[PDB]
Image 1: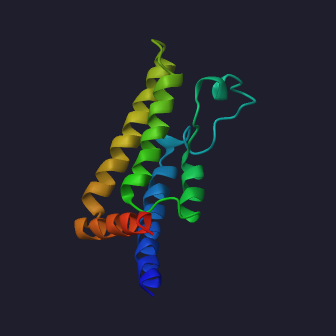
Image 2: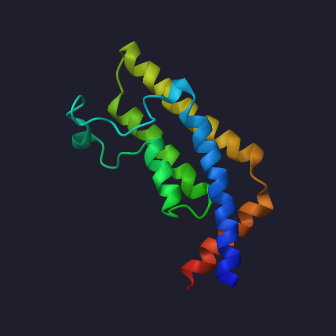
Length: 135
């Protein structure tokens, strides 16, 4: 029942991470990140990007209990952004549009968590993460 109680708290994190992801997913600036990059229309992607990531894959990850902290979640947002920048590094203002969007997706996600996540709640998640490592 410690397990039961721990699951309630992780559950509360998931509810919170779904609300955030949802606010990112419906912001029309982050449309290009809302879905996995198509290996039809963009055939060179999995050739250059080694770990693809997107807002809809993140939703799936929340539901598979892949995130026990807000930080594990932000890593994957960070990953969305670092891939954008790796695959789109050019002088062409199409690249710069995409990069500006990547960087704002990241910063927006970080400021949401920072403003809205109660710190003690986060500390509690961290120990549950750690306390599970140790089992």
